[PDB]
Length: 13
Image 1 (cartoon, rainbow, N blue to C red):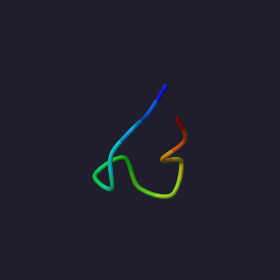
Image 2 (tube, one colour; image 1 turned 135 degrees about the horizontal axis):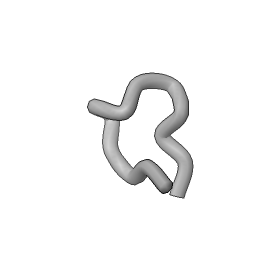
Image 3 (cartoon, one colour; image 1 turned 45 degrees about the vertical axis):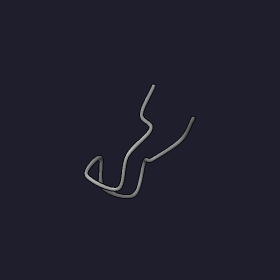
């Protein structure tokens, strides 16, 4: 649950 570089370092899809 996180598909962008604006998520931080938890950008996992």
